[PDB]
Image (cartoon, rainbow, N blue to C red):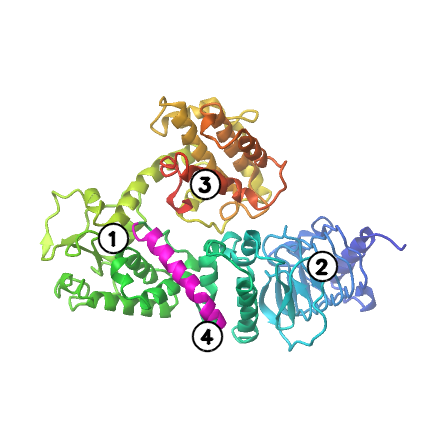
Amino acid sequence: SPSSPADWAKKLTDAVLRQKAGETLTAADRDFSNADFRNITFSKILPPSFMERDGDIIKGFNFSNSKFTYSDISHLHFDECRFTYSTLSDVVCSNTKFSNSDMNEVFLQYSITTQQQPSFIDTTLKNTLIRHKANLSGVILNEPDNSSPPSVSGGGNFIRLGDIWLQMPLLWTENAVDGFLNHEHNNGKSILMTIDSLPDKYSQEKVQAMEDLVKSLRGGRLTEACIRPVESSLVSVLAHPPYTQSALISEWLGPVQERFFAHQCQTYNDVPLPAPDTYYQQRILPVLLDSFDRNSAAMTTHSGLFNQVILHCMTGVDCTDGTRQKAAALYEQYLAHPAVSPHIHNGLFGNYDGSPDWTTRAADNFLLLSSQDSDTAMMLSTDTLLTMLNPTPDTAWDNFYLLRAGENVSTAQISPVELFRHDFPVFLAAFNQQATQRRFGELIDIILSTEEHGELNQQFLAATNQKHSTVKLIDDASVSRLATIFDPLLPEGKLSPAHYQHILSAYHLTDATPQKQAETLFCLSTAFARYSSSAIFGTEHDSPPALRGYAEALMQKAWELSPAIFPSSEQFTEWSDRFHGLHGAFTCTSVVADSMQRHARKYFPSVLSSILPLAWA
């Protein structure tokens, strides 16, 4: 006795149902101390107004020392509330909002199943254990005491974020690194982003918390391979002030940033960078500038990467003016480099004086160096350079002035694609990939009825234009869409042969060989796996069913052809499962999609690059 949460749920319901009906609840009426809420799905016992944007709030309630555990307060918004001494461990709080509240001495280690990320506005979290991924842009920090780091049955030591406790791992496994540091693999959710989110004013409680973390890494062993998956994630946050002014963070970052750069010069010097989204534009471009700044040699001997980085800094819509200025500056270097000097001509380049005219994109503002003959060069304008980089169905190529070295050299006898060959590898890749993005483009239309589901027919194509998609297709209106779209494309489980017939022809290869045919639509499966995984159309624990159906359909119809190309009879079964839930329900299909593609780039990798959007490679 007394009774279950089923009691308190009903009690709460009315309290707010009346609170919203106008009644200014007595304090006694809204005192819910020691309230049992475990396994309560508030979504099922409150009106929808309480979990929508506009928002009905839960104001003035006192849940001091209460139990939510396996509870679900996702999308709810608590205001002027006291949780002090309450546990919230294993609570699914997808996008929950706590404001003007007292959440002190609470155990806020919410369920990993949480999607969005809880946020705390003008709320205190004194001596409380939180997961290292809350939105704390409105959190109140007060000088810490001493007390005791909780703890319980978990893992490693604790560090303070002001008066907030955060729990380190027991040991930096590859998985530890991922859940903690890799916000790029987890829709912007890492311990990095978390402590970086505090108001630009708590700037020593932060630098502190980083330094502390950084230590627990310095104290870990972390082979140059543990940190490779996150070189970017890390450098996205700590290669910026206020962290640039530690000594630790600054010193520890050193190698990591160098490794970052080098890796980029290898990967993207002969190859197009996916048109930078708003994060890349704000957190990566600055860093590449810094690295080019500190390595003036690279500006020339990685002309490929450099130019790209500049164009993008100066075209990106979300680029801090600082970036735009530093990028303009660094180009002035380049443009005065003795390797480049000769190619620049007053009355020809940029503003006819010797610099670019950054005021009009029609201006011949770029001079790329050849990767073979340092004395041959291409001059072209911001507009044409953007389209040659991330092309379009009908993007012209023959649209530049060749310089050697010496004035304009006549085209109309030069095959631009044989020019890109060794002189300008970037465009080769762009042109080459544009050809492969067209066939796969056809399939997208064969299955999303040209202009019916025309909204989704485009959402799908847009996702192929870089590694991470901010938009996700998992709801109720969204799950219905695709199950009505793929269901008929696969009568009773497998691959409708009248559709295997479509995709026979529309990849310019009906009859060839089962060994190649298997590899072909295997890749197509690792393509649709990627579609349904995290980082694209699903979150780390919720992948579109139908997209996993179509994906499983494809590798099943790859097993009958040449199963000898696969890894094992264990793997097909191991994978073909996953697409259905016999195997947990987390790390998404980001394992299936990642591993299937990994077993491609080895054993038969030529086919991976002909179907697989460049951005997903």
Q: Is residue 192 or residue 83 the one in the foreground?
A: 192
Q: Which residues are magenta?
A: 248-270
For marks 1 and 4, the one nearer the N-term is 4
For marks 4 and 2, the one nearer the N-term is 2
Q: Quadrant of the C terminus?
A: top left
Dot 1: few (<14), some (14–19), or many (≥20) neighbours within 10 Å? some
Q: Give residue 384's mark.
A: 1
Q: CA distance from mark 2 to mark 1?
A: 55 Å
Say if mark 2 contacts mark 3, CB within 8 Å. no
Q: Give residue 245's mark.
A: 4
Mark 1 against mark 4, which lies toward the viewer? 4
Q: Indicate left or right for 77 with 277 as reference.
A: right
**Which secondary structure lies at badge 2?**
loop
For marks 4 and 3, the one nearer the N-term is 4
Say if mark 4 contacts mark 3, CB within 8 Å. no
**Which secondary structure lies at badge 3?**
helix
Give the residue type that dot 3 points to: Arg
Residue bearing the label numbered 3 = 598
Q: CA distance from mark 4 to mark 2?
A: 36 Å
Dominant SS of magenta comes to helix
Quarter where residue 327 is shown = bottom left
